[PDB]
Image (spheres, one colour):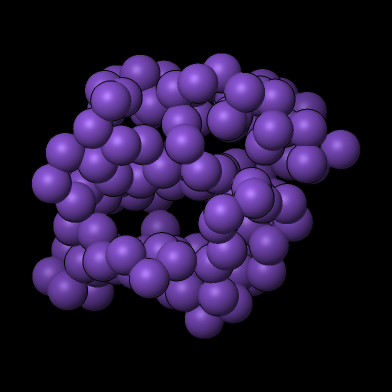
Length: 125
């Protein structure tokens, strides 16, 4: 049911346009219609959590878009591209990812992902 967390719990909220749930390895668990992240690109994100030295300076890519590091801790890596961007949140077993555009506010996006992450962590994922 990882597809429902995406269709309903993420994209369904309206706060995010595209979304996915990656494994700590980079391999996609579930994803939305027009979004895909390469294994290399996902394992690259899964690591910026151990040290964002690299993304902090070069930035990071997701599905062909080069994002700029805004925030980047050991649980949350945020990026932006003009007035759109992506929220990525690490759980105990996964990594949530939701992208937003100009019609959506960064905190609105950020809030939905953040909260869902809490819920899954509470569940053991």
